[PDB]
């Protein structure tokens, strides 16, 4: 399931990731940005072309 | 056309972009940081904490299984073991069948105490860099000051070896799988998953049975409460508990006669064997899917009622296995009232346990041994105990049956998210009350997220103070069924029969 | 004892704790985040930015090497090449020795223009995922609109192939290593280090020489300014520059006579060969330690002075190679005044270049060819140019000598740290003024940190407005020496002699 974040208005407080974790890592914005750049560059690549035969 | 993939044309880009540290050690608070750096203006609206729990201890109480009269399974078992011992010990014996069975139950409580202090000794060797809960959280959950075990290792080893030497001088049948079951539960560490950063299940006795021979009105097993988690009890307290346990048995003539009779009936290869302990002795956390299936379907029955319990409107409801020869034709009698939580008030969460239980299993094909082992820690209420008086603050329940042990509590050990990030002790039943305060909802949510880290954790039955409404089984179901009190009572009456079973003479 | 290490007992712990992503792509702004999350209250006191530059373009001007009279190395070279061509072309020739040498210099400016537009064409194929500066930053540094090269690829290819066809119809000796040197500098991409995320050095001509035959008073090579970085010039502008370059040579009778004479003297295997270009043609960034050693010791001389330059107190100081037959006995004359920065004011940073230069090399053993190639872009001032008039806003300098090319500027291309994180163009000399404003100190510090990313970057000579004080060579020295104007003038007079050298007839 997606990890949930639950804000309680009576407490002015959110609780963090509501999920069962197995083998995890804290991910920052630049790491996710690098992974997104890699995948979007991969998704819009055309191997039918002569670009790096 | 080339038709080679982008990831095959630049594999170094993919292997560089995905090099991340995994396998974070548990037992340690982690701060995640902010992705929006300006979000420190929202004080508690951004949760940057990540605490992983490591220990959930199942707090249990050994039982004979709901004796009402002389036709109970423990009285039939007393009859069969006394017929076996009596027709192997040709001579004049003075004890009855029930004195022999009460000796056997007191022997079981002794063996649970020995495996308990041996687990205290054998946990303290456990170290791994990837789990920082070892071994201090496991020692906090067992109720011992952890520094006392490290500072006084030789005195602790001598104490546990002398417990094994003294309590091992009384014979008990190893053909009874009752002792083998309590030894299996009571000196094993159990992972929820077969990984290295797995979370540990333990079994700690809430109370043990003290013999207490009295007058001429038979015998009466009375509770002896064990240390709870968070108590920093030292070696002298466990020595006092041991000496309180065997005060009426060491150097006693009748217990020696019964021990020699069990020795002559069941041979020396057919008695139980206590385990020795040295500085080499350590237990490792093993993966047992039979333990997890009965931890999953476990239902906590509450605190044991003692003589000093002040139940308003419920006098005489203390938990005791009695053997009065003028009452019930001299039958062993044990029928405790459940739903007591240590205080003199109602505890409205126990109303949530008045519905039928859910028996959940993995897979899609279930063996009969698998089904009957998965229901061993379950206990369903049947009626309400009748209040004797005008007013009554608590509400007690009577079950339809229970196994060789009932669950009293669970104790989860995690790390605190505030500095100095020391351990936290949380004690709970299957049922959980959330009263109307702001400091209860996020704390209850933290406790629920801590509980769902444990794979086959017991099923939760929460209730809310302002909603006046209990929610059902908070657990992920795979292949479930609805059990009724009669089916579970049949399974309990089968398993109490099988645990107290001895062979014949031929 | 065991004496095995902790890292050998738990290697998985070490390999898990040190798995980090490296090889970050350059051409991309990176935000580092905060380690103290509360530090957003300090607005600019916490620098969370990280911008890596990718292109430093050396902006140069081809020279013959400080002609003062008829005993100059270019006039001796004119004499030798005219003796060679004249005694291979038995017949009646009408041109002098200096018309032939001026034809050869105009041929050099043509070849630099062809390699320039061919580099514009061959850069646009360059892609790599780990450097996002390719190919748009390299096209911005060359002064071309990058989208025009992509949208009009066939028109660009036709234009560069027709430049090679037209300018390749005039003969020039390939025994002269002058043309080979300008071809080496002007169509190569050079990394500062032999890595994949390396930073690129380029050479772009600031100006070229237009022939401009006039009247009867000989010839006069005049500057033709090339596009600067940040100008988004299109193909029509480069076509206008080309047609302005060869307006007086295409279909000309005297240039055809001189071209046929160079063809007959130096055979068809001994002429220079321009390179063709197609969609297959691309240049790759190579590692050349000879390029880096002269980029390191390069000293920028300033902007070229034109007719439309308005130097207050300095009339007639425009840069021009002249061939007046009534002046200096008809000698080729070129002696430019340096220290002009495009504006009509003093430019106090050029006072920092009035000290002796430092010649820095790697290693500890230096070859004579290595030493003389490391000094090719260096140019030291010797005296001040004499102001002719009452007042004078600029200050000009006269060198002791210079090589076949002088450096005018450098242009560094990096990414902006503010959104939308587009490219930034920074043009600088070796000398840098920091006037007293708050928006100059951190910007100058950013520029210094951008410059020290380039390995053998030119040595900086900063000066401060309120301190009235220049600081010396801002560069890391390895094995240095102090050069004087006479030693560098000897090396320049050797290298101008070697570049314009032709063999004998036998």
Image (cartoon, coloured by chain):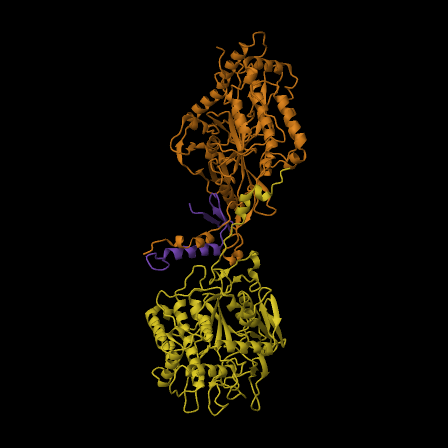
Chain colours: A purple, B orange, C yellow
Residue B313 visible within the image? no
Give the image location of residue B440, x and y in percent.
52, 44
**Quarter containing the N terminus of chain B:** bottom left
Residue at image location 56% in from the left, 65% down from the top: C44
Indicate the quadrant where residue B141 lies.
top right
Residue at image location 48% in from the left, 10% down from the top: B506
Q: How many marks?
A: 0
User: Which residue is more in the foreground, B147 or C50?
Assistant: C50
Q: In the figure, B11 relative to B488: above or below?
A: below
Q: In the figure, C370 relative to A7: above or below?
A: below
Check the image and name the residue furthest to the front: C506
Give the image location of residue C48, x and y in percent.
54, 61
Indicate the quadrant where residue B226 lies.
top right
User: Which residue is more in the foreground, C292 or B49?
Assistant: C292
User: Which residue is more in the foreground, B230 or C304?
Assistant: C304
Indicate the quadrant where residue B236 lies.
top right
Q: In the figure, C268 relative to B441: above or below?
A: below
């Amino acid at each position: 399931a997606p990890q949930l974040y639950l804000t309680y208005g009576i407490a002015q407080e959110s609780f963090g990731p509501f999920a069962q974790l197995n083998d995890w890592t804290i991910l920052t914005g630049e790491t996710l940005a690098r992974m997104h750049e890699v995948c979007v560059t991969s998704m819009f690549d055309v191997p039918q072309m002569g670009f790096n035969k | 056309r080339n038709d080679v993939a982008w990831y095959a044309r630049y594999p170094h880009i993919l292997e560089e972009a995905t090099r991340l540290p995994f396998a974070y050690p548990i037992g340690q608070y982690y701060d995640t940081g902010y992705s929006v750096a300006s979000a420190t203006e929202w004080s508690k609206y951004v949760d940057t904490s990540l605490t992983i729990p490591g220990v959930m201890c199942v707090n249990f109480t050994p039982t004979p299984g709901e004796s009402y009269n002389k036709n109970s399974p423990i009285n039939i078992a007393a009859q069969n073991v006394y017929t076996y011992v009596r027709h192997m010990n040709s001579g004049h014996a003075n004890y009855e069948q029930a004195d022999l069975m009460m000796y056997l139950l007191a022997m079981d409580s002794l063996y649970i105490f020995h495996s308990y202090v041996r687990k205290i000794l054998a946990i303290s060797k456990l170290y791994t860099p990837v789990n920082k809960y070892f071994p201090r959280a496991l020692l906090v959950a067992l109720g011992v000051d952890p520094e006392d075990v490290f500072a006084n290792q030789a005195q602790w080893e001598y104490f546990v070896n002398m417990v094994a030497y003294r309590a091992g001088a009384f014979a008990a049948p190893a053909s009874m799988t009752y002792y083998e079951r309590h030894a299996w539960m009571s000196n094993g560490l159990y992972v929820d998953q077969d990984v290295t950063r797995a979370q540990i299940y333990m079994f700690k006795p809430t109370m043990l049975w003290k013999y207490e021979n009295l007058g001429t009105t038979g015998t009466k097993l009375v509770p002896l409460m064990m240390p709870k988690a968070g108590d920093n009890r030292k070696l002298v307290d466990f020595q006092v508990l041991f000496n309180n346990l065997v005060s009426t048995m060491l150097g006693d003539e009748d217990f020696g006669i019964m021990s020699g009779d069990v020795f002559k009936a069941f041979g020396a290869d057919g008695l139980v064997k206590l385990l020795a302990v040295d500085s080499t002795t350590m237990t490792l956390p093993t993966y047992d899917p039979l333990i997890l299936a009965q931890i999953h379907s476990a239902r906590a029955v509450g605190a044991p009622i003692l003589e000093t319990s002040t139940l308003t409107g419920f006098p005489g409801r203390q938990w005791q296995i009695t053997q009065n020869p003028d009452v019930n034709n001299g039958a062993i009698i044990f029928h405790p009232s459940f739903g007591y939580d240590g205080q003199d008030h109602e505890e409205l969460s126990f109303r949530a346990m008045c519905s039928n239980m859910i028996l959940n299993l993995p897979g899609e094909a279930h063996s009969a041994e698998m089904i009957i082992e998965a229901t061993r820690l379950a206990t369903m209420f049947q009626v309400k105990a009748v209040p004797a008086g005008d007013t009554s603050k608590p509400v007690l329940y009577l079950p339809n049956g229970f196994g060789t042990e009932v669950v009293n509590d669970y104790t989860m050990i995690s790390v605190d998210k505030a500095t100095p990030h020391d351990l936290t002790i949380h004690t709970f039943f299957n049922n959980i009350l959330v009263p109307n305060a702001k400091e209860n909802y996020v704390a209850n949510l933290e406790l629920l997220n801590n509980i769902i880290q444990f794979d086959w954790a017991p099923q939760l039955y929460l209730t809310y103070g302002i909603a006046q409404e209990s929610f059902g089984p908070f657990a992920q179901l795979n292949d479930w069924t609805i059990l009724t009190g009669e089916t579970l009572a049949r399974m309990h009456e089968v398993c109490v029969t099988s645990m107290f079973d001895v062979p014949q003479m031929g």
